[PDB]
Image (cartoon, coloured by chain):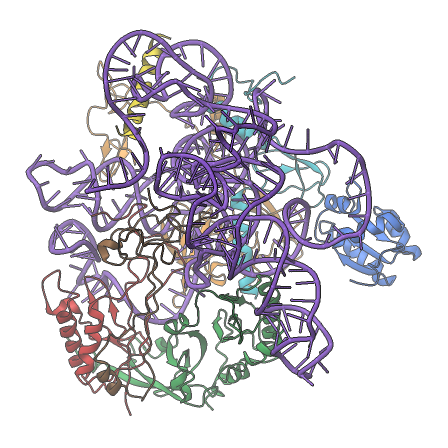
Chain colours: A blue, B yellow, C green, D cyan, E red, F brown, G orange, H purple
RNA sequence: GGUGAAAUUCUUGGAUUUAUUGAAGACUAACUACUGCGAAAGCAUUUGCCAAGGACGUUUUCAUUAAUCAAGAACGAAAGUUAGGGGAUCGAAGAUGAUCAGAUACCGUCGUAGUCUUAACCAUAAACUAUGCCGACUAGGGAUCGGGUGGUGUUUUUUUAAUGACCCACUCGGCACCUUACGAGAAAUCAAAGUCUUUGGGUUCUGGGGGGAGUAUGGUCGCAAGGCUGAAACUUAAAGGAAUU
């Protein structure tokens, strides 16, 4: 499931929450995979996808809202997009 | 000694007695 | 009272090339007068024939096909696939108590824009040397078997258009590889196919439908 | 402190207008005064303006719907049947 | 060189139906039925009435040289009785004796998946 | 009072109730566990089959039966002469 | 004066440099900034204007045109729509389910917006005060308050007059009755509790 | 069209039926069993998602954290109530046609509320296994659900590697059965309803003749319908349970 891997990443690997941390992370080049919610504004996720494919970064689509994304990652607030710099003890980069 | 119909008649008597009580109070 | 027979004519129908037999009966049709034009009223019609009649053998007795007419040409109207069904008098035979019934359904497309509703039926067999009484299913093998049978039939229909789907449905090789590829789940006897329902159609598509009678 | 035990929202009407009238408008006022979330942000900020108006102060999106509920069961069933028909034609 | 048809025998209760028609089903012939040859309100399903109905159907079948006809016997269906009427056997035997070719029998009574709750209520009919 | 178990219901679940078929004594059966009397009566009764075999345009084939799973005999089949009233030798079978 | 909202959609002129501001009946489930697809070759989505001749049976459509070119006749009140039963390829017509439960057959070239008009179930909350009714009817016409004809004067109404109060004659009025006598029930086939 | 027999009703404007469909609602038939889950009510299509639960195996952990329940909270069949959606079949009321001395009952046809769902009430049943929960022992056998163990077990192929289907022997947890009664019971019967005069394992609740009466009143919850607690006056020598002719 997505939630267990997300929790394993949030416990071991580094992470940036929000928009601008994510954009600086990817733009510098450390980001390996980004997570975009379903209720994200089209233009927003479209640009994210453009940045990822120009920077050669994998893209995964999450069906749900920002609040459930926050609950899954382990933070009670809401998050529109997240990126993983290194998996750590996880293997989400290999599979999926 | 039909329990159901005598029981229903008992509730009708309850209705009438409640109406009589509500007439004064 | 007028005589309907003198006001009506006879018509002959030929089965598609999917079945080697051609003639599938004789349909009574009113004369196509200019006021009514009964010729175009024949487009929306179906004809139900037995597979045993359409094959000349006796192992197709419990199989039959309804055959929708597509084009009419000088008392020689030709027909096309509409949908087959297992006869209910026979369909109540192989189903018995003290055994498990298996039913799977799909909405898989084909190569000619047709959409079909394919179902299938599988049982559990009282194996040889058995001493038990019912040989019931574990209830989770059905969960494990439903996915594979749907997968194997969907991959078979995909990549093959309607013509060879029928040309291989009549021999009933579909249940041939079901048992051997699933010998590790249940004995799986009586894997005869079930109804196929065709929901949405493309346009008339003149010419290509002639090839089934060309 | 919960000054009113059962009257709730409709305490301004006082003693008159009866009981059924006040209780019905009360049930309607709970749902029509409730805070909703825009389907595009997720924050509880949607508020009712005019009749059939579901405005917001943060998402800045107005979604037309019921005069007192942003999405009724009729909306759910009509969306379901319309998407069924759309799938059937587009299949 | 024989011409076929569909007789679609409808064996119901208190009435019997025979309808010889082409395989297409959009054109039918000989609407004669069990009640055609009797006026009793209680002998419609009797074997004699069914035999007379089939004899009339067979006689009218060969108007312009119709040889054979398929049959498909059905009951009332729905959720009422789910069994063929007594006159069904007499109906299908009369025309067969009359020289009419019979074959490809098929039990076309409709059966539901426990739907459309039938007439009677919880306690049903009582006599 | 007789009828310890009454019917075969020892577990729970209550099942459901199906309509009774052509009895004129239809009612809510005590669960699906009643007298069944499944019938495999043929579409054609005995005799008169020689006429059908000869009149068949094609040879052999045919001869199926009616496959009717019945649940119509419940607490009123004594009128219909199906279930026989018995005595303390009822220990046979269930 | 309308419980249902108004959808203001701006179109693009395909003939000259201009953008047309259209006033549409606001359906439910449609939000500002979403693209309205007005035409025949569009897809079955809420807010689309697909004609009933290019849609299958059973679809829910609001703001149904009676005839082509009328530009809005049927299904204009909040919480109402139209259901399609069937269509005939010959002499193109569409069978519709009228919001009154009536039967009407119209041409297949009639446009309608897919969905249900917003503001459904508007008449669920009573008006309580006379002020709510007064404000409701101030925006429509001078039809409030309405006086009973039984507390009237003999000259003022046929139903009035008398020391006591009573209707006097039968309240049902024939369809062929002249103007002036049509006071009460008009062509009432049946009356009483339904 | 129907009933034992009839009748209402629909039928040249085509009744009923058939063939092509389309739309609406409800259910999950056959598979359905002295076969299975849930505390109870209750659960009988496909697939995905979420969490929870019993049993099994453990040479892993805590350490007696444990059993029953006044007052006290949650679920809770059908029916009923509030406001929407839906409203196809059936259908409390009702409208009709019978039979009947009488029939607003049984019988045929329509038919509102209701039968389905949503948010909130209703807290009731032959809600029965009429048998409370926890723990221990006691004559046997067979079948069955889930798990596990051993036997080159018989099968499945690419005989054979495996899996899974079953065979044999056994185990735990069960729902439960068949023959007998050491024992109990007034008997019907019970592997407990046994281990109660040879009377005592722990715990909660209920009843002291039948009516009055689950009634009066007083409290309490409920929109209402209703639910919980709950008498007295007066009357009778019989009410009631198992089997026999």
- Please name the residue shown 38% across and 50% down the image: F7
Percent from the top left, x then y, of residue C43? 39, 77
Percent across and percent down for residue G90 are: 39, 68
Using the rendered image of the protein, determine whether residue C14 is visible from the camera's viewpoint.
no
Q: Quadrant of residue G106?
A: bottom left
Q: Is residue H232 above or below residue G139?
A: above
Q: Is residue C177 left or right of residue H238?
A: right
The answer to whether one can see residue D57 in this image is yes
Asked whether, in this view, residue E104 is left or right of residue H36, the answer is: left
Percent coordinates x, y for residue D62 in the rendering: 65, 41
**Nearer to the camera, H100 or H41:** H41
Where, quadrant-wise, is the N terminus of chain C in this rendering? bottom left
Q: Residue furthest right?
A: A28
Left or right? Give the position of A69 relative to H121: right
Q: Nearer the viewer, residue H91 or D47?
A: H91
- Relative to the observer, which residue lies in front, C6 or G138? C6
Q: Residue at x 28, y 88 (%)?
A: F57
Above or below, H106 relative to F24: above
| Residue at horizontal 62 percent and vertical 18 percent from the top | D2
Q: Position of residue H49 (x, y in %)?
A: 67, 53
Q: Which residue is pictured at 11% across the width and 70% down the height?
A: E37
> How many marks can you see?
0
Q: Is residue G125 left or right of residue G91?
A: right
Camera-nearest residue between C81 and C165: C165
């Amino acid at each position: 499931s997505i939630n267990q891997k997300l929790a394993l990443v949030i416990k071991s690997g580094k992470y940036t929450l929000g928009y601008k941390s994510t954009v600086k992370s990817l733009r510098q080049g450390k980001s390996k995979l980004i997570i975009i919610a379903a209720n994200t504004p089209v233009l927003r996720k479209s640009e994210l996808e453009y940045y990822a494919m120009l920077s050669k970064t994998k893209v995964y689509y999450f069906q749900g809202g920002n609040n459930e994304l926050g609950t899954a990652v382990g933070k009670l607030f809401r998050v529109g997009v997240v990126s993983i710099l290194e998996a750590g003890d996880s293997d989400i980069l290999t599979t999926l | 000694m039909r329990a159901k119909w005598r029981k229903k008649r008992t509730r009708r008597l309850k209705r009438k007695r409640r109406k009589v009580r509500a007439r004064s109070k | 009272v007028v005589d309907p027979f003198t006001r009506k004519e006879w018509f002959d129908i030929k089965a598609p090339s999917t079945f080697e037999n051609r003639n599938v009966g004789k349909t009574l049709v009113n004369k196509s007068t200019g006021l009514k034009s009964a010729s175009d009223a024949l487009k929306g019609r179906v004809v139900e024939v037995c597979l045993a009649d359409l094959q000349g053998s006796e192992d197709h007795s419990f199989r039959k096909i309804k055959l929708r007419v597509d084009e009419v040409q000088g008392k020689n109207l030709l027909t096309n696939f509409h949908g087959m069904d297992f006869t209910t008098d026979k369909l109540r035979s192989m189903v018995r108590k003290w055994q498990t019934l298996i039913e799977a359904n799909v909405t898989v497309k084909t190569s000619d824009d047709y959409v079909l509703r394919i179902f299938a039926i599988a049982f559990t067999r009282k194996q040889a040397n058995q001493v038990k009484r019912h040989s019931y299913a574990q209830s989770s093998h059905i969960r494990a078997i439903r996915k594979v049978i749907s997968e194997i039939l969907t991959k078979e229909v995909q990549g093959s258009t309607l013509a060879q789907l029928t040309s291989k449905l009549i021999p009933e090789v579909i249940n041939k590889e079901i048992e051997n590829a699933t010998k590790d789940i249940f004995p799986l006897q009586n894997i005869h196919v079930r109804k196929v329902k065709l929901l949405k159609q493309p346009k008339f598509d003149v010419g290509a439908l002639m090839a089934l009678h060309g | 402190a919960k000054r009113t035990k059962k009257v709730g929202i409709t305490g301004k009407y006082g003693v008159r207008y009866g009981s059924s009238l006040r209780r019905q408008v009360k049930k309607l006022e709970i749902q029509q005064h409730a805070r909703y979330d825009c389907s595009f942000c997720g924050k509880k900020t949607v508020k009712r303006g005019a009749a059939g108006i579901w405005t917001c102060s943060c998402c800045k999106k107005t979604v037309a719907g019921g005069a007192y509920t942003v999405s009724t069961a009729a909306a759910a069933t009509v969306r379901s049947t319309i998407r069924r028909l759309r799938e059937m034609v587009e299949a | 060189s024989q011409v076929f048809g569909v007789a679609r025998i409808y064996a119901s209760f208190n009435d019997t139906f025979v309808h010889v028609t082409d395989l297409s089903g959009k054109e039918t012939i000989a609407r004669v039925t069990g009640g055609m040859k009797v006026k009793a309100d209680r002998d419609e399903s009797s074997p004699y009435a069914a035999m007379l109905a089939a004899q009339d159907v067979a006689a009218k079948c060969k108007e312009v040289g119709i040889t054979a006809v398929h049959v498909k016997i059905r009951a009332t269906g729905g959720t009422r009785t789910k069994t063929p009427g007594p006159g069904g056997q007499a109906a299908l035997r009369a025309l067969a004796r009359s020289g009419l070719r019979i074959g490809r029998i098929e039990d076309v009574t409709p059966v539901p998946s426990d739907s459309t709750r039938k007439k009677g209520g919880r306690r049903g009919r009582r006599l | 009072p007789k009828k310890r178990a009454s019917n075969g219901r020892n577990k729970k679940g209550r099942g459901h109730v199906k309509p009774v078929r052509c009895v004129n004594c239809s009612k809510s059966i005590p669960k699906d566990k009643a007298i069944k009397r499944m019938a495999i009566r043929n579409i054609v009764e005995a005799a008169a089959v020689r006429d059908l075999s000869e009149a068949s345009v094609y040879p052999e084939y045919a001869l199926p039966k009616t496959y009717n799973k019945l649940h119509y005999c419940v607490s009123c089949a004594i009128h219909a002469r199906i279930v026989r009233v018995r005595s303390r030798e009822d220990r046979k079978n269930r | 004066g309308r419980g249902a909202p108004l959808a203001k959609v701006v179109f693009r002129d395909p003939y000259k440099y201009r953008l047309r501001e259209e006033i549409f009946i606001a359906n439910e489930g449609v939000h500002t900034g979403q693209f309205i697809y007005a035409g025949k070759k569009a897809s079955l989505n809420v807010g689309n204007v697909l004609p009933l001749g290019s849609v299958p049976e059973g679809t829910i459509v609001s703001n149904v045109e009676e005839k082509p070119g009328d530009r809005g006749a049927l299904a204009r009140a909040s919480g109402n729509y139209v259901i399609i039963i069937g269509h005939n390829p010959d002499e193109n017509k569409t069978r519709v389910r009228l919001p009154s439960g009536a039967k009407k057959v119209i041409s297949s070239d009639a446009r309608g917006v897919i969905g249900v008009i917003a503001g459904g179930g508007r008449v669920d909350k009573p008006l309580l005060k006379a002020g709510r009714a007064f404000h409701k009817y101030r925006l429509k016409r001078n039809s409030w308050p309405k006086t009973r004809g039984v507390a009237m004067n003999p000259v003022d109404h046929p139903h009035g007059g008398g020391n006591h109060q009573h209707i006097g004659k039968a309240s049902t009025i024939s369809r062929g009755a002249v103007s002036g006598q049509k006071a009460g029930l008009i062509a009432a086939r049946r009356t009483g509790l339904l």
